[PDB]
Amino acid sequence: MSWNGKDERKLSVQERGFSLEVDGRTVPGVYWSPAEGSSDRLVLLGHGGTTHKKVEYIEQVAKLLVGRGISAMAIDGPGHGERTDVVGLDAFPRMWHEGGGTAAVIADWAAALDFIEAEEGPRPTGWWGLSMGTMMGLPVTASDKRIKVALLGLMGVEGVNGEDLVRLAPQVTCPVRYLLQWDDELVSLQSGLELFGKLGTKQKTLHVNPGKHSAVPTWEMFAGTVDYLDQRLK
Amino acid sequence: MSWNGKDERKLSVQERGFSLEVDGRTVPGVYWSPAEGSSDRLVLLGHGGTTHKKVEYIEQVAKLLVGRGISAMAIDGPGHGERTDVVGLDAFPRMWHEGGGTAAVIADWAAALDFIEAEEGPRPTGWWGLSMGTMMGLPVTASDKRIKVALLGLMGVEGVNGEDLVRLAPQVTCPVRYLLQWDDELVSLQSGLELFGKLGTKQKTLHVNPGKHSAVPTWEMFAGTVDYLDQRLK
C-alpha cells in the first residue's frame, strides 16, 4: 500500500494516485479531496463495466462530492483500468472471473479503505456505484460495515455475479438508494426489481426513470445522488 | 359556484369553503391560502378512499404548500365527504359508480378550477393525490392541460376505474412523480408498475419504498412531494 506519485491539484480538488498489493494482485487507486483543507466524510466510487477508476462520470461525481466537503476514492475492478457500458460486452464475464471475482473485489476494497483510513483518519464512509459499481458495491457494503449508506443501481440478479448479489443482498443493512432504468437493455427491469427486493435494509428506496442503461437523468445521477449521500452520510 | 361561508383563519393559513352545482351534483370544496398575502401558484389535492377533502394528511400537505407560497384546493370525490384507506372497502365500487364515476370527477374538478381561477386569478397549477387521489388525478391531469405537474401514486390498473386509468394514462403529458409501496396490500406492485408504464410523459419518475399502503415514509410523502412540486411547478 503506497501513494504512487501520480498526483495533480485540481483546482480546489486534490487528486492523488496510489497502489496496493493484495493477495498477489496489484490494486491501482485514486483519491480526491479538497485542496483547502479538511474533509470529514468519504465516499467509495465504483466504476460502471469496461471502464476504470478515473472514467469521466466517476470523476464528475467525485468533483461534486468534494464540493460538499466529502472526499472520494476509487480503485480499478477486476480486469479493468491499470489492472457504452462494458457489462454489455461478451468478453466481460471472463474479465470478471480472471480478476478473482467477488471475493477479490471485497478484499481489494477492504485494503484500499484500510489504507485511506490510516493515511487520512477513519471517517463516515458511503458507497456510490452503478452497474459494475453495484456488482462491486453491493458485496462491499454487505461485507464492510464501515459503509454507512450506499447509492447502487443499474444491476439485477442476472448479472455476471448475480448469485453473489442475491446471497449478499440480505446482508446490506444500511440505508440504500437504488436506481433503475425502465428500458435498460442490459439489465431487465424485473431482474433489477428482484435484486432490490432482496436488500435486507428497511431504509431502501428505488427510483425508476425511463430510458436506456446509459440514460439515467443527469439531475438524478448528479444532484440527486450527491444530495442523498450528503444528507444521509453522517 | 359560491364561497359557502365555512371559513377559518388558520394561523398564517386562510381556509375558505365553497360549493358548486355541476350537472345536477352538489360539489363541496375547500381552499387554503396564505393569510398574508399573495400566492402565485396552486395545487389541487385529491383525497385518498373513504376519506374527504378535509381529511388530515391532505390538510398537512396543504399547510406545507402554503408555507412555500402555494395555495391548495380540494373537493370531495364521488360518494364522499359532504356528498385505513377506503379503496379497500367492499362498498367502495358502488360508492364510485353511483357518484358518476370518472366522467363526473373530471367535470367536477374542471368546474372547481374554473371557480378558483375566476376568484383568485389563473396560476400555474399542479396536482397532488394518492390512491383515490390518483383515481381522480390521473384523469384530471389527462383532461385538463392547466395541470402542469402531478404527484400521483398508490394506484394501479386493477383499481375500480382501472380501465379509465389505462385509457387516459397515455394522455398525461406533464411531468409526474409516482409513488408505490412495495408491500401494498391494496394495490399490487405489478399493477402499479403497469399503470406507471402507460403514462405518456417522458418526464416521469417512480419512487418505491418498502411497506404497506399506509406506510409511505413521511419524508417521501411530505418534504419529498412538496419539494418536487415547489421545484417543478412554475
Image (cartoon, coloured by chain):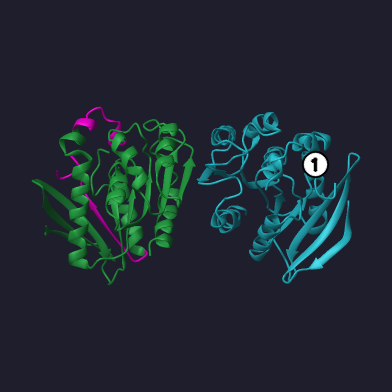
Chain colours: A green, B cyan
- The answer to whether residue B199 is magenta is no
Few, some or many residues within 10 Å of mark 1 (<14, 14–19, 20+): many
Quarter occupied by residue B136: top right
Residue placed farthest to the left in the image?
Answer: A24
Three-letter amino acid code at disc 1?
A: Pro
Which of these two is toward me, A129 or B156? B156
- The residue that appears at 73% across and 69% down in the rendered structure is B37
Which of these two is toward me, B100 or B211? B211
| Image x and y of residue B35, in percent | 75, 69
Q: Where are the magenta residues, as a range?
A: A68-94
| Image x and y of residue B62, in percent | 69, 59
Q: Secondary structure at mark 1?
A: loop
Q: The N terminus of chain A is located in which quarter?
A: bottom left
Residue B74 in the image: above or below residue A86: below
Q: Subunit of mark 1? A: B
| Image x and y of residue B144, in percent | 72, 41
Instruction: Read off the residue under disc 1.
Output: B78
Q: The C terminus of chain A is located in which quarter?
A: bottom left
| Image x and y of residue A75, in percent | 21, 50
Is B107 positioned to the left or the right of B141 in the image?
right
